[PDB]
Image (cartoon, rainbow, N blue to C red):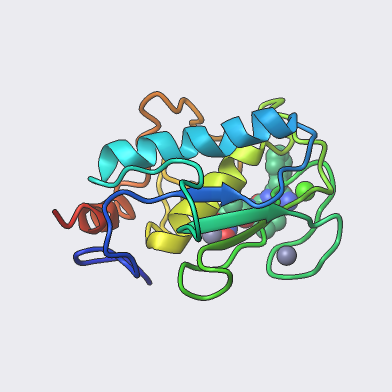
Length: 166
Ligand SMILES: CC(C)C[C@H](CC(=O)NO)C(=O)N[C@@H](CC(C)C)C(=O)N[C@@H](Cc1ccccc1)C(N)=O
Ligand SMILES: [Ca+2]
Ligand SMILES: [Zn+2]
Ligand SMILES: [Zn+2]
């Protein structure tokens, strides 16, 4: 497990993400919105303030890809999960690859570029793996994607209470 205290591998409580690429299916624009939303309430919980790439490097950068790349999770094509992501520090710091195999969709999900985002974004920092109802860890895209107040994992939130160092 990652996270805490005084935050992960960042000396800022004002971070960023970067959709390196953005597969133009949701569209690219609604894929940015799938991510950017996820981000938004992750910044209500911790003291952090996430946003898209202010400059330089980021926290969790993401590229789309996995039509069948073969990293972690499965390139399963449109439908299923999709992110074959791995941790903050390890990978292009906070690395996640989202099935460009999909045709991003939010038809309940099918696949929506939003939870690959949540799973990734929460995965990197340290709100990484649990088992609840609403959590980023509630483990199969049919989520509580009401990202107005998504209310992340309550356990992996106890790690966002670290991000929250200040
Ligand atoms: C983003 C979050 C939802 C990821 C979860 C849980 C997780 O944290 N795994 O590490 C997941 O990977 N679930 C996969 C496991 C594996 C394939 C990587 C799954 O059950 N996927 C469904 C996809 C799905 C989606 C909608 C309807 C039906 C089925 C499946 N392959 O049966
Ligand atoms: Ca898939
Ligand atoms: Zn990959
Ligand atoms: Zn996971």
